[PDB]
Amino acid sequence: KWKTVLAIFLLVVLYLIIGATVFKALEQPEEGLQKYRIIQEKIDFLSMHTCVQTSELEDLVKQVVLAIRAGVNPSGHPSQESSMWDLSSSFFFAGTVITTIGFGNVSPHTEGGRIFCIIYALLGIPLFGFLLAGVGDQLGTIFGKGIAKVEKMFVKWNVSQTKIRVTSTVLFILFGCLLFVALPALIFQHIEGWSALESIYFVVITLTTIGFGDFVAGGSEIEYLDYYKPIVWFWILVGLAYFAAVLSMIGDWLR
Amino acid sequence: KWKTVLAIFLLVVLYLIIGATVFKALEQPEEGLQKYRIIQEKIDFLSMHTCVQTSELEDLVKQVVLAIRAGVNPSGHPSQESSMWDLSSSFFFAGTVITTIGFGNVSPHTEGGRIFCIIYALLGIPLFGFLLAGVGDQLGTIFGKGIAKVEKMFVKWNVSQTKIRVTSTVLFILFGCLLFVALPALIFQHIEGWSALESIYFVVITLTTIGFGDFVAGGSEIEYLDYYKPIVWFWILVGLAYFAAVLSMIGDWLR
Ligand SMILES: C=C(C)[C@@H]1CCC(C)=C[C@H]1c1c(O)cc(CCCCC)cc1O
Ligand SMILES: [K+]
Ligand SMILES: [K+]
Image (cartoon, rainbow over all chains, first blue to last red; front, side, top):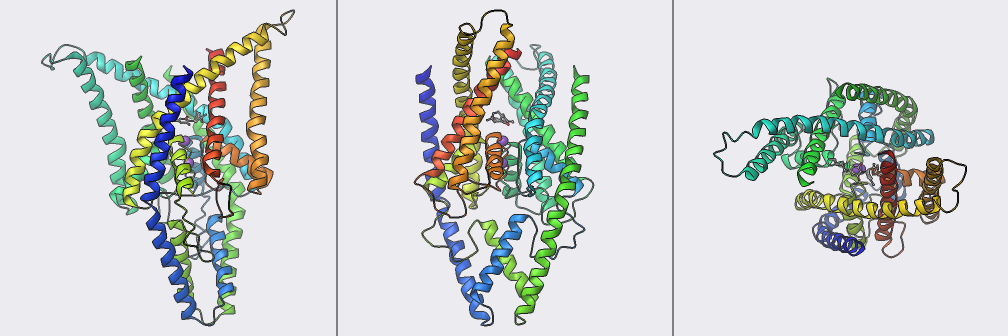
């Protein structure tokens, strides 16, 4: 019904308004303090060296931010051997493109690169969706067979059959979340030296296909080896397949 | 069958390998040239001002990159009034979070904001998905009725009705794409002053929900119209609803 659709739309609008207000209130001071700090640091450095011209310093900072947007780190002197568009890195980038994650830490800069990226995404996304649906359906069929094994009126004390089904689904999703969210969060927390909050935020963002780009699996050149990019892409695929299977089972229960 | 699923998996692996190879081959020279350019510009800046120590220069570059990761504009002096986390930008950020776009030009740096960002995404993504599915279902139903009407009013003799339906559906797809890609491309080619290739790249990324972040509707502090971010998000919403309805009709015909 059109009225129901408009009611849902208005609810979404109210949710967005509330989220915008709370985000503004919970972020304004941080960036205010950062602006104050960078302004006072720039003034102190200009007073430190009278030789440096302020316009020249601004030109230098402009070139630094241009290089940052290009995708090369100016703070560390590059040896050109650790190419950012490495073969494993390119494989990870293509995997994220077809997965609709889009971290954006590395982006194509050539015009032909942009055209090829557009064509590649438009061709690959339906194929990846088809594969994900197939694997999720396979895992859902296996889980349904497991539930049919569970439905035996035994080792449940006959409390409530609906409670038993709900408990089985909850245990399945809990075990899957523990296997594919918390444990990879700990692994990334140890490997990348981040905090637990940072690692769990990275895992949630990556799996939910958001891809903010503030935290990337490969960054700051700390010698990721043993095909780190292929295995992290494989973990992404397995987790997404599991979540798709759980969603398919949930849709089966709802309908 | 699981066998053809594994075959599709091998096809996806091959596609990713080919894409990675082509991307690396295309994007090596740009990063190489940028590395050499930044190295030679830093040595030139050291030559111009012998007072500056190279370690202090790299420290200043490190501070600039840290401010870039913070989200403020390092070049020039950021005005205190120019709060990046204002109402309109927060509304756009919340909309992109629920839509799963995830551009990444802005992100909650405060730990409290991060926790709320995780909870907000987890709650809002299902609601926006349900709203999009409902709007797509309604629009697809009226599309099917209208296409059946115009099919059985204009051409009814000496042809195949399936071919007529396919041709009319392709015509509608093309017209909707031209009204939802080319016209926004021109609008962005005026307000944002991007080249036509950049505008179509931005539209393709935005509607696909890749969300690279190299191009953002509101950025560079170039000044925009009142509540430009909400209206551009509304454009995103409309385009996504139309394309979801079209794909639903295509799936209905396929089924
Ligand atoms: C045409 C694409 C690429 C689809 C469908 C239409 C639009 C506007 C966006 C895309 C999209 C996802 O790519 C992924 C999800 C959620 C996946 C969750 C997996 C756990 C939703 C979702 O709408
Ligand atoms: K997405
Ligand atoms: K993204």
